[PDB]
Amino acid sequence: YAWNRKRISNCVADYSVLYNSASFSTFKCYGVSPTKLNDLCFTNVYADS
Amino acid sequence: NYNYLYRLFRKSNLKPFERDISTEIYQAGSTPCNGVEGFNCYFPLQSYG
Ligand SMILES: *[C@@H]1O[C@H](CO)[C@@H](O[C@@H]2O[C@H](CO)[C@@H](O)[C@H](O)[C@H]2NC(C)=O)[C@H](O)[C@H]1NC(C)=O
């Protein structure tokens, strides 16, 4: 109910080794494109983990 | 009437006046596709309820 809103953005979301690791779940996302996350920067994305 | 089908997604873009009957899915997210095709390969075609 009190999910976080930390603005984890304007950074580098590299996923090379992330995709290599088989234990990982899902980062090939459907928002804009699965791979548009390595050098892409985020405007005001807030983590709600 | 699930006899009417539609494709989930196509690797290549659209193209005027052509038909594609591809029965294989791309290397999608988790469980992208076993080998080339087979199990754990989301059917690139979906029906209509
Ligand atoms: C947090 O946990 C995740 C998941 O284990 C870690 O992500 C992995 O980190 C290793 C290298 O440290 C990579 O080889 C993997 O590709 C990553 N994804 C996995 C295992 O699914 C992450 O390193 C951890 N971060 C911290 C600060 O603990």
Image (cartoon, rainbow, N blue to C red):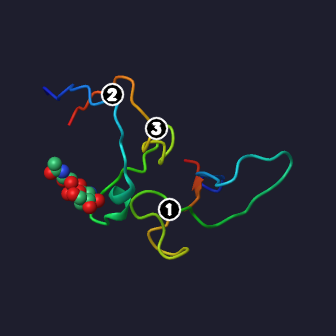
Chain designation of label 2: A
Q: Residue at x 84, y 53 (%)?
A: B18
Amino acid type for the residue under numbered disc 1: Tyr
* The image quarter in which residue B20 lies: bottom right
Is residue B19 depicted above or below A30 in this figure? below
Per the image, the residue denoted by label 2 is A45
CA separation, marks 2 and 3? 12 Å
Per the image, the residue denoted by label 3 is A31
Residue B14 % position (x, y): 74, 46
Q: Is residue A18 left or right of residue B28?
A: left
Q: Residue at x 13, y 26 (%)?
A: A2
Q: Which mark is residue A38?
A: none
User: Could you classify mark 2 by the number of other residues whose Cα lies within 10 Å: few (under 14), some (14-19), or many (20 or more)?
Assistant: few
Element on which disc 3 rests = loop
Residue A30 % position (x, y): 46, 43
Amino acid type for the residue under numbered disc 2: Val
Q: Earlier in the sequence, mark 2 or mark 3?
A: 3
Q: Is residue B10 left or right of residue A27?
A: right
CA separation, marks 1 and 3? 19 Å
Quadrant the C terminus of chain A occupies: top left
Q: Which mark is residue B42?
A: 1
Residue A15 % position (x, y): 37, 51
Chain designation of label 3: A
User: Could you classify mark 1 by the number of other residues whose Cα lies within 10 Å: few (under 14), some (14-19), or many (20 or more)?
Assistant: some
